[PDB]
Image (cartoon, rainbow over all chains, first blue to last red; front, side, top):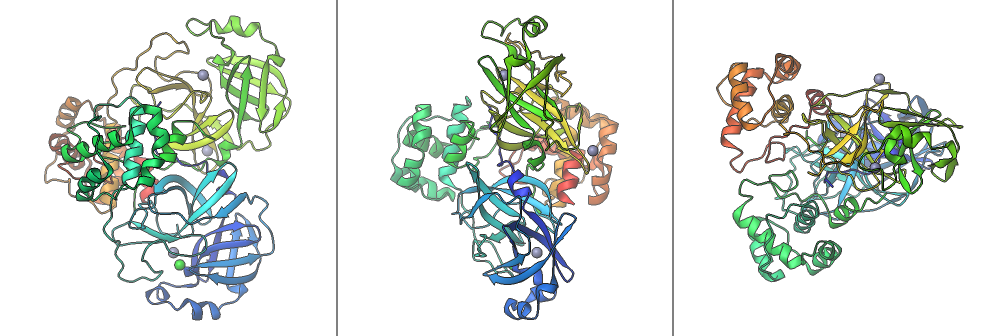
Length: 304
Length: 301
Ligand SMILES: [Cl-]
Ligand SMILES: [Zn+2]
Ligand SMILES: [Zn+2]
Ligand SMILES: [Zn+2]
């Protein structure tokens, strides 16, 4: 019993973190095989970030401009290239601690663990979701650029995020490991606003199932609704539409608790209209949307 | 910017997790040097749940009755002893991944990271606090016994918790690594209940300072309070009394934000009176109490 915001064990990723310096700019890098991946803005000063031409900034640099440190050991840079908003530094040694890994791009609503790093040193690990507006509500301070987000499936690390910046509202933006931004953002110190965010409906539903599994049943309504009638009420409270795909994804949890998906939708519809009436669900006074149906099954099934 | 329930990187503890089996009971063990530490109830059969005499159950065991597995390798048990509620299994091989470590006993209100494990394999990591009633609000299923709680500083891993049981309310109980239970709990399946859980006041105040550091001040007010009037009000909401030691511990956060401790106490009194009114603080619609003043400082600066 119990339900927590749980992150993947971070050991496989800790062995990949390095410090990358270019001039006076220092951030984190990810060392896999004989390559170090980091944000392309490592080649910028504060002044360059106002309006950078990364093509020109990189063309005016050589292997000598980059200093990579894996703890106390310096790694020799023998090649460099840019792939979108990430810089790839070829080094003379393959990381002996390279785990089985792949680079994956996630969709809004999906979750991942972040290993916050400073000067190549891991400081903490936490779980977050990619918002429908493509930002992440992280916890990052200066020097955290290059920190990565990941999931683990069996013994394979799927890297999905590399941290690049903080937007005016204090939320965060980054890219996948191939340097493609999530969201309509650019790596430049300019006026950038995160769009209006919405609630990940399928995740709130999965979390209501976790609450039932843990004995919280006060909110249950069994006057079955339809997907169409639920969506009409849901869109009014800034909730993402619930697709039939989402309903199918909720199948295993529905069978486990004896609560049909459209009965949980009826329960959520009333929760939106009434509010929580001074009550809590799983230790929260709001409807949590950063747990996917797979996170709920995994945590309520003890998968390793 | 931002504020999250952050755990310590779990790598150094993952390299210590092993599986321990005695008969048909399997749980987790912690392998440090040539010793594996695990809950002593690994020696219990179905008839030993209510009133086990562990000294009598253990005297009947030989080294070869304990099966220890680290990955795909069986470790040979060459000795065994019991210290309070933990069993120490001496093995013939020292863990080459043993980090620098210490065993510490934490106090209520303090936080630590838990590495949830099943069959010696880590499944996830989360942060939690020792409640004033000496229970933890963890996330543990059948097979999680032996999972540990820890903190990391600049030199060592400080192990502070080993998981042993779940209570009827869904909360958890365990011991330090010397086998001493936190609270009045025992390793028996007799009906036990956790005392009234109160809110960790000093932690709520630390979290309000984190909200101010992160740019939010909506909840502040123009008042102050004496420490006694604050305690008389806060105790009516099941909050633990705030001591002068707690006031002094909040000093650096008070100096960073320019908000006197007793002025933050006045804000907290008003928040208890009014609630959130549809607002949130650091993404929460409740007053959060599982962040210590040090967790706030680490994350905010
Ligand atoms: Cl960049
Ligand atoms: Zn940066
Ligand atoms: Zn057990
Ligand atoms: Zn230490």
